[PDB]
Image (cartoon, coloured by chain):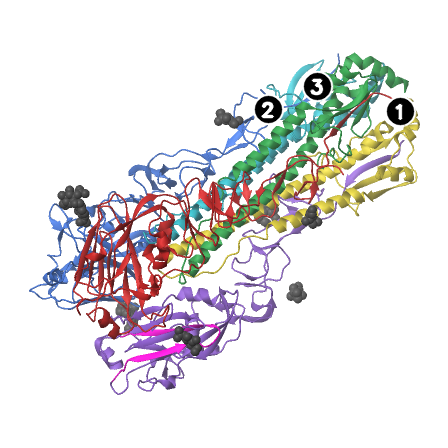
Chain colours: A purple, B blue, C red, D cyan, E yellow, F green
Amino acid sequence: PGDQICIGYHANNSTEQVDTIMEKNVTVTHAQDILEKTHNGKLCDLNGVKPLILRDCSVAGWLLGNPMCDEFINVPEWSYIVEKASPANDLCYPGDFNDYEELKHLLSRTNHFEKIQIIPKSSWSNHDASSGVSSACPYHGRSSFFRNVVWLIKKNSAYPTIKRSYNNTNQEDLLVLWGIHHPNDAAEQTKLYQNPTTYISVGTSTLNQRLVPEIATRPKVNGQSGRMEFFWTILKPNDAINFESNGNFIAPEYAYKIVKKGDSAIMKSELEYGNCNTKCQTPMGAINSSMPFHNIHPLTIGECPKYVKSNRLVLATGLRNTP
Amino acid sequence: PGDQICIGYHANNSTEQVDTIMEKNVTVTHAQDILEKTHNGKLCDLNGVKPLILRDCSVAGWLLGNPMCDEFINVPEWSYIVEKASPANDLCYPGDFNDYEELKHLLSRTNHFEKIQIIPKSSWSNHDASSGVSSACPYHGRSSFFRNVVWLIKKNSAYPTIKRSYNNTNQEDLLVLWGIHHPNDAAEQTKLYQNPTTYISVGTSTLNQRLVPEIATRPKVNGQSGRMEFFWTILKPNDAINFESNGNFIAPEYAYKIVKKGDSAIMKSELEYGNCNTKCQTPMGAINSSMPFHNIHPLTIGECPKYVKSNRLVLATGLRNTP
Amino acid sequence: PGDQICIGYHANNSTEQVDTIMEKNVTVTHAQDILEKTHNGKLCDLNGVKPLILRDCSVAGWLLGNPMCDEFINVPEWSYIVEKASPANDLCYPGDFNDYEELKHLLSRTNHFEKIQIIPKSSWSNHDASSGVSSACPYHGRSSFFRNVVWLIKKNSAYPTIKRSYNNTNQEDLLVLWGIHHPNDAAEQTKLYQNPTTYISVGTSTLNQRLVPEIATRPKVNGQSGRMEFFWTILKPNDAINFESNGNFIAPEYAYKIVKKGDSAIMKSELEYGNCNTKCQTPMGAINSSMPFHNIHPLTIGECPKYVKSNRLVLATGLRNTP
Amino acid sequence: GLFGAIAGFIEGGWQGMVDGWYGYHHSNEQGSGYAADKESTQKAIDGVTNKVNSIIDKMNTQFEAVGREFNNLERRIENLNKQMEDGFLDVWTYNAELLVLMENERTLDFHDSNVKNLYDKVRLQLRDNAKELGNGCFEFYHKCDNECMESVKNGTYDYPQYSEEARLNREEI
Amino acid sequence: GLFGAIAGFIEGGWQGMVDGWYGYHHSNEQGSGYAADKESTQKAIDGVTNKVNSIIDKMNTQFEAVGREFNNLERRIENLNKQMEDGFLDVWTYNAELLVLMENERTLDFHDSNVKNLYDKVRLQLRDNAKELGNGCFEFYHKCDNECMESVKNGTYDYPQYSEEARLNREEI
Amino acid sequence: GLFGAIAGFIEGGWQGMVDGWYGYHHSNEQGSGYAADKESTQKAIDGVTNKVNSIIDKMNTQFEAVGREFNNLERRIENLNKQMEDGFLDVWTYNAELLVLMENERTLDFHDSNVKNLYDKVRLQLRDNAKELGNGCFEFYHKCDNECMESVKNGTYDYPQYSEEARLNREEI
Ligand SMILES: *[C@@H]1O[C@H](CO)[C@@H](O[C@@H]2O[C@H](CO)[C@@H](O)[C@H](O)[C@H]2NC(C)=O)[C@H](O)[C@H]1NC(C)=O
Ligand SMILES: *[C@@H]1O[C@H](CO)[C@@H](O[C@@H]2O[C@H](CO)[C@@H](O)[C@H](O)[C@H]2NC(C)=O)[C@H](O)[C@H]1NC(C)=O
Ligand SMILES: *[C@@H]1O[C@H](CO)[C@@H](O[C@@H]2O[C@H](CO)[C@@H](O)[C@H](O)[C@H]2NC(C)=O)[C@H](O)[C@H]1NC(C)=O
Ligand SMILES: *[C@@H]1O[C@H](CO)[C@@H](O)[C@H](O)[C@H]1NC(C)=O
Ligand SMILES: *[C@@H]1O[C@H](CO)[C@@H](O)[C@H](O)[C@H]1NC(C)=O
Ligand SMILES: *[C@@H]1O[C@H](CO)[C@@H](O)[C@H](O)[C@H]1NC(C)=O
Ligand SMILES: *[C@@H]1O[C@H](CO)[C@@H](O)[C@H](O)[C@H]1NC(C)=O
């Protein structure tokens, strides 16, 4: 009999469901997904700057210059570094890298190393800078050695005291590597470096250490039963490093200019380059998303969504939809 | 005069109170307590697996084999480990246990040690393995020494160079302990091991050390003014450990096979066994609860409620009760 | 025209704004600011106990007694300690301070040092305790040295073996400092301490160490090319410390009695005293507030509001105001 | 409360209704008695139960403290470790305490809302066929037998069936 | 929901209404049709959009995990570091998941409130010039053309204008 | 807002009313004036005061940053330490900012609700003895002197006292 007006609300064919405290799977007209769950599964540039992918080399193998890591003899500026879990080409000659992790940390705060010759191998007039070579570090079928560091061995049955010094004349910090050799027994000791008891002394404005070789009988690792122990320091732009040793010294030839310090990272991932580009990278792959969250992997680099462990994050935006 | 219908809500004789942002102590018809506040004040077995209770022994005392710790010569599998705050029976002969904390950590990731004789005490033909004994380490009132480790002493005024080697043929990691003796003076040095300057070198695929005893005069601790320094390493399944020494060597006799690795813990508690069983254990006692929260103690093991610092957590479930 | 009653709500000329999840800048009738944003820019006493301001001396400079740090020869009980980012007077003679951070930490748990002479400087009858002085540590233009530690040098071309001992008879812990000198070459070694090859051994109920000087040629820092390495220990109330050395020993003269243990801090700030008193202190200034939050600096000491990184925290208490 | 029903326009609960949280008290010629609205009660029970279960669920990934040991020269990381543990313990204690306080407040208002909705459910059915006494009770303008009472309670009130006898009773008033 | 409108006294939404969240369905002699209430709809769009943006803004200072490596004798601090990283991930996951739950609920009740308020906006205008059917509809006591309808929608209904036309239709029935 | 009263069916607040949050404006032959409802204003004051204190209280077990030093070969743990301190600072900042945003919304809605409740308190008393103008006012179907007004304000309105003169004025219109 009469005209009427009704108040009502939207409804549609949406199936989007949403959770709240009191009810779960509440179908709604409109929702916004805020959780990213997909990546391209490849390693990419970070804003157009290529990462340093070590393939089968470890950071040590790279810096020390394991002959099987020649791929990296001169690496350009990088955004991040990718290292496999258990790289095959690590220390070809068995041993240790002192404060290795503290060095990897310093690497992750770095984007550019420029290799420079700090002590020419040719300049070792009174020692043998050529037989310092092992089958544990094979190159092209013949015994070789770490390329940035030199295994000085006695010449004409005499090992004169070494007193070499390098003054950093660059404007950059420079990373210097050196090492000490731990022989198997006193015979081998006398065989390689004439003197029976030796030391390696290093001096810097801040550094002062004197390393002495610790002989022991060890199982053979990569054929060798001796060990080589590696050390490092950062030489400030106007500082100098002073080496004095009478044996067992694995001397530096090449050091690294720290050209660009910035924010970087060392990613553990097993995958390789994909020739793509992104603003956000993860160990499982890269992310191109406008979502505020993701559940891919916690360890990321670049402008990223915030990592969260959810399988699902959905905001209700519309209202309760009617069946 | 007329028929009527009323809308109303439940009420009862409840005195249960609940808190909110705007109001405190709100009597309510029904509430759920979600905070467990009681424990049995006892240390108990965890899911049918008894804990290892060290009583008055420390982990060092146990593993090195303090004679006052004979209860633990061959301990069965454990669920968790209980150690007092300041156990009396630690290192009976004074000294240090290197990387001890890192060793306790390894333990806490372990459930079962099977002790094995790695170097028989009988095999010391040209050294004295019988006089390595002290009143600081009393057995049954008689001077003795750590049981799993051997204090080798000169024989016929001679301490020949020792070269023992052990290859782990088991399928498990093996925990090997050894030591060095630091005497009071050059005299004591001579009296015990003939040779005046000594060393101990240990070799492994990964381990390389050469220890030299540091002679000094130190205060008397348990009568002794010398010191013993203990070391450990894990010997991987096809690896071998090489000892070479010409004095001050405290030799391994027994080592420990890591049979079961699991999730365990070293609970610091002053209490002892209770012959009971539980599913959740804390250093103050065990928890028998279905509450999602507890406030007994933060450090727990087993299926446990989540610890919280509240005195009270009660949810309103019913509605505001009327007086 | 009939009688009427209206229900309505308060309004005023208030302009205070407040934020909510759905709406920003909501003008409101009454509001409470709960964020404190102001400080007096001064370092003050903390509840009637004055702070220790190190000015340009570092903790090392203070404790070792750098000649330019005479202000701190006898410091009273303190509330907290203020040290600059890069204090000028640190180790005047170049070198290192062993476990320095752990020592700074122990300090932060301390309110009172009472300096004590443990072995008087005069008592070195058979060594030279007087030429142990350097130009690197100038006093008032005159060459001097650390005041609490003595640089023992050979006397009459002889450095007899040192055997000194001190038994803590006090009721308090005692902080003992000593050091070792690292010369430039074997020549200088003999020049200063007769014996060519040397050691320094320290013994305590808990401590056992034997230090050997590590010679190297280093760049000159403060004119000196040598290095001094400092060590510390806490001597328990009935324990004794035993020094034995034949050279390169930098001996203790003054040690520190820990009179008051409490809760303290080492504040890094560049500003100095303000002669005021407070219950809450920050490295940028002091706080007089009843606010539950502040945003000045995270590192605070005393009864303080909770630090938070917000620019604004304002609670609505009143209601939405009308234009 | 927020919705004006519980301890509001309905000033008090009924000890007498015991088979539920919300319901009716009727009064006709056949006699009076309490009865719970099964539907709105079950809805509330489901809501509160899911709420309780959701609170306990959200807390399964909470921090769990671990025993760790340190020596006299590891005081810094010892303290760092302690601050870390207390840090998370304080956060999660806040989270549990606050969550309970916040959802308690919402729960009380939730019940208030269920009641106010129940009252409105009846009111919107009865319209001018009954008088709002203003205390949660509606005085009928017609005869409401037990079956009629049951129709109001299960949302099947036939308004026009009683419309005429209601209208006539309104107008002699 | 909390406000009794959506899935309450207004049982069900309108598939037919497609240009907004809340609105009107009229039916007179000139014809019937759906029309969206733009102002109250826009107001919600403003509210929910700010809400989503404000949640996203509050989560920008979230924790970000960093790679750190440790050696075989640094197991304690390795474990401390993993416990801390997991600690914050768990804290921040809880924070997001709970905030989403809480605001989802409030967003649904917000809509319920917007509808209930729109219903009241009309009800409070029309008064005794129309009858509450009890299902979200108002049956008029007079003739309401398209011009009348547009006045109700924009809050310009003149109660006394029809009071007399309406009064007549009340009492003859 | 959520409850449709503040900035809703009651459009605008009163500058004139200064002794409370919610209250009345009456208008009879004896004169008009603003007056504060003591009960509802005080109840609100208690609620917000308790709220501010509960917020201040729950934040006392908050994280406290401590100075810790690390050297050039302790960069990893220095970094871990910074991440942890920053981590907790970020958590408590979120916790305070968010808690403030959330209770601010509810504080506003609490007031809105308080007004709608006060209005209903009066509405449920007066019933048909007055007409709802729809702007927060009730125009009486009788004469309400100052003492009658006072009766409405303190919840003691005698409906049957004015019932007959109200009915008479209802039926003449
Ligand atoms: C919510 O919807 C999903 C179905 O899409 C259910 O989610 C759980 O996980 C998968 C998803 O497909 C289902 O197969 C499981 O059966 C579900 N388990 C649970 C939680 O029951 C879920 O069942 C729905 N919610 C409820 C309470 O029924
Ligand atoms: C420890 O002992 C095992 C067992 O004899 C050694 O493993 C053997 O290595 C040889 C190569 O020399 C293989 O041909 C055998 O098959 C291995 N035996 C078994 C059963 O595994 C191992 O090399 C020894 N380790 C060391 C370094 O002493
Ligand atoms: C440091 O000096 C104290 C004080 O004399 C020594 O303790 C005393 O030792 C003697 C003999 O052992 C006893 O007769 C006294 O009764 C002891 N005094 C106390 C405190 O009871 C203490 O042994 C010394 N410390 C060291 C390491 O030599
Ligand atoms: C993001 O993804 C799109 C394709 O989905 C593509 O344009 C590219 O990968 C990214 N966008 C940009 C910024 O180029
Ligand atoms: C809550 O009640 C208890 C007594 O059971 C008491 O501890 C407390 O005072 C009450 N809370 C307040 C302050 O209202
Ligand atoms: C809030 O108000 C202040 C000025 O009073 C200003 O900083 C800000 O721009 C305002 N917010 C928005 C959303 O514009
Ligand atoms: C290094 O060389 C530069 C330039 O000749 C000089 O300024 C500096 O003193 C040297 N550094 C040291 C301490 O040897």
Query: Which residue was labeled with disc 2?
Result: D19
The boundaries of the magenta stretch are A158-183
Left or right for E16, reference A206: right
Tag count:
3
> Which amino acid does the dot numbered 2 rest on?
Asp
Image disc number at residue D150? none
- Does residue B109 appear in the picture of this structure? no
Q: Nearer the viewer, residue D141 or A220?
A: A220
Say what secondary structure mark 3 lies in.
loop
Query: Which residue was labeled with disc 3?
Result: F154
Q: In which quarter of the image is residue C133?
A: bottom left
Say what secondary structure mark 1 lies in.
helix
Query: Which residue was labeled with disc 1?
Result: E170
Please provide percent x and percent y for residue F5.
Answer: 74, 33
On the rendered image, what quadrant is the C terminus of chain E found in? top right
Measuring 92% from the left and 26% from the top, which residue is drawn there? Answer: E164
Marks 3,1: beta carbons within 8 A: no
Whether callout 2 and callout 3 share a subunit is answered no
Marks 2,3: beta carbons within 8 A: no
Magenta stretch prevailing secondary structure: strand
Please provide percent x and percent y for residue C274.
Answer: 48, 47
Q: In this view, does A79 lie above or below F10?
A: below
> Which amino acid does the dot numbered 3 rest on?
Asn
